[PDB]
Length: 10
Length: 99
Length: 99
Ligand SMILES: [Cl-]
Ligand SMILES: [Cl-]
Ligand code: NA
Image (tube, rainbow over all chains, first blue to last red; front, side):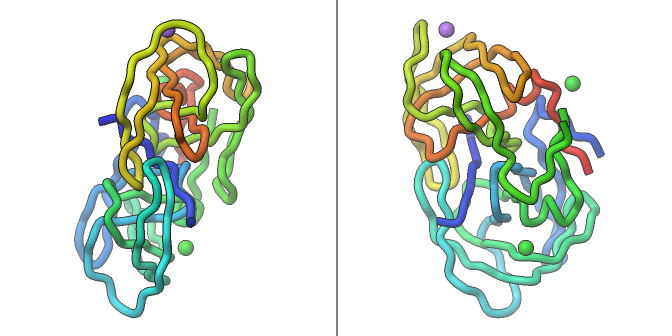
């Protein structure tokens, strides 16, 4: 329940 | 405000008249919210992160309040594990990282 | 420094004697780096992200330098699409979000 949100548009 | 990072930087947002919790995410290019109804037409987008990619619905020029600050911009809707406020809206509310 | 969010907030880090580029990520609980060797013991871990879960190796008490600033903490190594500095080390360099 480590959550890690890098996010980019594919 | 000045927000330290000992806990997740969770804030209240207001979108479509309702209050939700979301995470301020300097590692997110975009803003992504859990399934909800939004007005108007949408366009397709794919977004990637740890884990892989997901399909989302892109809605433009959506009125959204973030911790009390007004923004109007693009909101992605889909099966994200968490509501995330990304740099497109963090820049609208004048947020910076400081150390 | 004060870092704006018009572009991804990337910095140079030194870890395991190597220089790398990493994303300062307030929406990450943990620090996650692409495959590399680190000294000492490790244990397996599953972490989530947009996308789902990935399996990583967890190394504790790893010294890192982030944009000039020394810290120590846990580092996760595995198939992340981006090196990220998460909150466990952002706190140690005194990073805050401000708006
Ligand atoms: Cl936008
Ligand atoms: Cl502090
Ligand atoms: Na160790």
